[PDB]
Amino acid sequence: PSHVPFLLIGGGTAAFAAARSIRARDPGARVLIVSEDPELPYMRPPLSKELWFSDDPNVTKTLRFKQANGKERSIYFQPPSFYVSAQDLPHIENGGVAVLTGKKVVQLDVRDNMVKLNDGSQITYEKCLIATGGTPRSLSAIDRAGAEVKSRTTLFRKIGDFRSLEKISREVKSITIIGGGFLGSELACALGRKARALGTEVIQLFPEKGNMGKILPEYLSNWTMEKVRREGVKVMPNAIVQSVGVSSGKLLIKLKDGRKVETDHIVAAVGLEPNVELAKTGGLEIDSDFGGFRVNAELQARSNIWVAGDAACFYDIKLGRRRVEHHDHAVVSGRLAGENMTGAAKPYWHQSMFWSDLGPDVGYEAIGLVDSSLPTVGVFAGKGVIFYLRDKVVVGIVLWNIFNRMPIARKIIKDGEQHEDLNEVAKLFNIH
Amino acid sequence: KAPSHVPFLLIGGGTAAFAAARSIRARDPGARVLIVSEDPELPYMRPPLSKELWFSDDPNVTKTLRFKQKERSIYFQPPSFYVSAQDLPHIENGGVAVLTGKKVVQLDVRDNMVKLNDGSQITYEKCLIATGGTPRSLSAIDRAGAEVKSRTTLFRKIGDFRSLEKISREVKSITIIGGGFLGSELACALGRKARALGTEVIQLFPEKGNMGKILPEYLSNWTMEKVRREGVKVMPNAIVQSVGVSSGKLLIKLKDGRKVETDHIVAAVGLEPNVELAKTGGLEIDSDFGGFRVNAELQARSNIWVAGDAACFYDIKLGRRRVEHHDHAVVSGRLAGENMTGAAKPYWHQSMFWSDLGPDVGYEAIGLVDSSLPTVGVFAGKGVIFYLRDKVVVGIVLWNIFNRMPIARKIIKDGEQHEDLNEVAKLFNIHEVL
Ligand SMILES: Cc1cc2nc3c(=O)[nH]c(=O)nc-3n(C[C@H](O)[C@H](O)[C@H](O)COP(=O)(O)OP(=O)(O)OC[C@H]3O[C@@H](n4cnc5c(N)ncnc54)[C@H](O)[C@@H]3O)c2cc1C
Ligand SMILES: Cc1cc2nc3c(=O)[nH]c(=O)nc-3n(C[C@H](O)[C@H](O)[C@H](O)COP(=O)(O)OP(=O)(O)OC[C@H]3O[C@@H](n4cnc5c(N)ncnc54)[C@H](O)[C@@H]3O)c2cc1C
Ligand SMILES: Nc1ccnc2cc(Cl)ccc12
Ligand SMILES: Nc1ccnc2cc(Cl)ccc12
């Protein structure tokens, strides 16, 4: 299309939430999503969890899964019939939402409210949302290695990554995961379950002393590492990769402490790099501390440009400047951007929550500023709650195997109350 | 009496506010603009307070507040240009009203409302924060007694010019603490006045020379000699340790062995941005440069802009900055007013600053001017200083070269990597490289 009122750059979780937010407040809105991926907007969490614990051997083709409730759903937010074609977008009665897949915005002209695509096309907009997300980081050791090593290394984020790694797990006998965060630990439990049926091997190495060493306190991180080992995973904590090479066709990971790991494939889950390529041509400011596009409390960068999702470094009126990489955050920030793109002028207020499932026995939700560096107070009874403190106020909460009580945690963070006894606060989560 | 509602609300009654009011009115001929000023005076420009008003021939200059540039007043406009705040929502085609002697003490961004120090509440449709900044003080003078604090002057407002002018006619020794442009301008002003009364003027600062933070050492040293020849006792490399009163006179004890006895002290040691309203308003402050953090359009939130000294903004060409120049307050205020009327345009036109150290020394500058940056100077009495970063000119200082600032502005905008800066110097009519 030559011109479109609402232009959403990127076809991920934040863009879809913004589109349906715009449509809700402007029933006749014409919204164009431009996505470099060939897929329609879809959610990613199932790519490292539900899709691996499915009984259907065609799950790689159907891309459907059963939720905690039990109802089956697809990873796509909506079926193709819910969208309109970009050709019909500036004609169809009552407008709609179109997705232009396989196209990447490569130049942003803020002055003329115009974007240029990788095929030379130019599109003008009235209001634009940057929801480009981010790219998985790689390891310098794997970068210094040859093509043989890189060709046997997976960066997990997209649907293709799930289908390729699922295919690898059925072809090799040993897969090593590098990274102790949520993604690395979830893929370990997933491959561990998948490995128990074929008798294969799953290794996980990371620099910390336990899984989520940057997020959970030491004692809980250590307890988690044992739960992951119970899933059939060989966990190698305190491991820093010095170099990676190929010897006799097998991958050989040399660690800084002298240890060596022989494996067939490597999955690198070592953080995310925000896609801020369009800031150069667009003259958009990026945040040197947190990375990403720097935006205000309303997720706004310029008069008619907002940013949401993983790529948005925003100002939290309550918690300070932040950048968050959570699914619910992309939904909340995307939804908020769409509202502000229709005159709402609302600041980021409703905090988002993140969750993670390390097998069917372990599952944690969380909200706010969750960092192992901050002081923590853990109350337990298999079940517990972790409070994250700063200036004598609770700024982050982790709920360990406690569900359907996130609104309670959200209220504690908002009230900013100075609690004399957190043990009493733990009763709000049914801990006694 | 302030109206309960006003379309445009400008907080602060300084240079940035006035420029925004003119801008708003030029784009919305019926705009109703309310300025709220904690000062009792109408908006006025400050550069004359340290320069032209001291070199005036009129002995009534302290009363008239007029100077020759053509003669004009320090006020941007006479009271006739303004309407009253009470009649602002009734006058046909609106106008600009100034509510003096009132301070905004609370900012509710959610409800687009402010609260004044008297309890008055004013809602707005669009708002500009133009609060400027407060002069800093020295910890040594903060630890001193009331006698010292009573004999210390923080120079910024009209009252400071009138109080210091009367003191220069009553005491024998005035010491200026601060080697920046303000301290140097006041030294040349008091030195010119002291040569006629037989008094003394002292200027001390920690740097090796005047404007040591701005100009290269060789140019800062040359400037210190001209200030000295204006009849000033300049004391470089001076760090104050304590200040006290002895035998009715002020005694300044420096970190080294030197001691200075004087009658009055003038501190020109920088500015502190007035960001008090950021707490209640939930507005972000910049921890590096200070001030309110705003984007390239000077916007903080949907209906709140910030201009002037208090605005930490994003320069698409030069990076995040905060500038404390008169022309910047004009340019950034005019830009804010345009954006408050839908312009949606970024800070693009670079502001210039200038300084006159007597009638024989005149500096003009533009861009990122910092002595820490690598510099290249080309001279012929006159010269140009190029401030470099990434092999590109990011700042220019023009030494006794006038009516060529648009040329300097183009060099910085073009971002060209010049193979020879002597050829670039010829654009300023320079034909000694340092
Ligand atoms: C495997 C996996 C599991 C996860 N599990 C969880 C979980 O359990 N809980 C949780 O809270 N979070 C989870 N997350 C994080 C959550 O998925 C992310 O926060 C969320 O996907 C971010 O959405 P987004 O809109 O910000 O960006 P993205 O989802 O990254 O979407 C951006 C899209 O824009 C495209 N794009 C980028 N640049 C351009 C351009 N110039 N032009 C056009 N298109 C462009 C990108 O290709 C991508 O398609 C998981 C993430 C992954 C990868
Ligand atoms: C003596 C002097 C000489 C100078 N000479 C030069 C020069 O030669 N060249 C040059 O380039 N620059 C010069 N400057 C710098 C230039 O004057 C400043 O950059 C300019 O005045 C900045 O304007 P502003 O509108 O941002 O703020 P200000 O001029 O400080 O105006 C802010 C006003 O808002 C008021 N205010 C603050 N908070 C509130 C509140 N909550 N409610 C109501 N009112 C409030 C303050 O009292 C003040 O009256 C000089 C400055 C001084 C002090
Ligand atoms: N369970 C998760 C919680 C938060 N963030 C995540 C990011 C990734 Cl990439 C994968 C899983 C996550
Ligand atoms: N001549 C000046 C140039 C730039 N900035 C100045 C700031 C002050 Cl406070 C006083 C004079 C100045």
Image (cartoon, coloured by chain):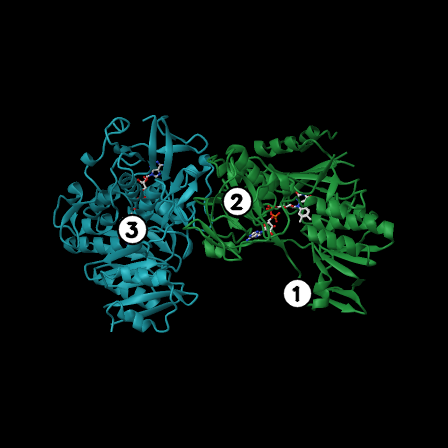
Chain colours: A cyan, B green
Residues at discs 2 and 3 in contact (Cβ within 8 Å): no
Q: Is residue A285 visible?
A: yes
The x and y percentages for residue A211 are 31, 60
The x and y percentages for residue A152 are 29, 44
Could you say which quadrant of the image residue A125 lies in?
A: top left
Q: Residues within 10 Å of mark 1 (few under 14, many from 20)?
A: few
Badge 2 residue CB within 8 Å of ligand 2: no
The amino acid type found where label 1 is placed reads: Asp
Q: Is label 3 or label 1 in front?
A: 1
Give whichever of B33, A363 is nearer the camera: B33
Give whichever of A234, B277 is nearer the camera: B277
- The span from disc 3 to disc 1 (Cα, nearest Å) is 51 Å
The amino acid type found where label 2 is placed reads: Phe
Residues at discs 1 and 2 in contact (Cβ within 8 Å): no
Establish if B2 lies above or below B240: above
Q: Are marks 1 and 2 on the same chain?
A: yes
Read off the chain for label 1: B
Identify the residue position indicated by label 3 in the image. Answer: A328
Identify the residue position indicated by label 1 in the image. Answer: B142
The x and y percentages for residue A229 are 24, 62
Identify the residue position indicated by label 2 in the image. Answer: B313
Q: Is label 2 or label 3 in front?
A: 2
Q: Is residue B217 visible?
A: no
Which residue: 57% across, 37% down?
B22
Task: State the quadrant of the N terminus of chain A.
Answer: top left
- The span from disc 1 to disc 2 (Cα, nearest Å) is 31 Å
Q: Residues within 10 Å of mark 2 (few under 14, many from 20)?
A: many
Q: Secondary structure at mark 3?
A: helix
Q: Earlier in the sequence, mark 1 or mark 2?
A: 1
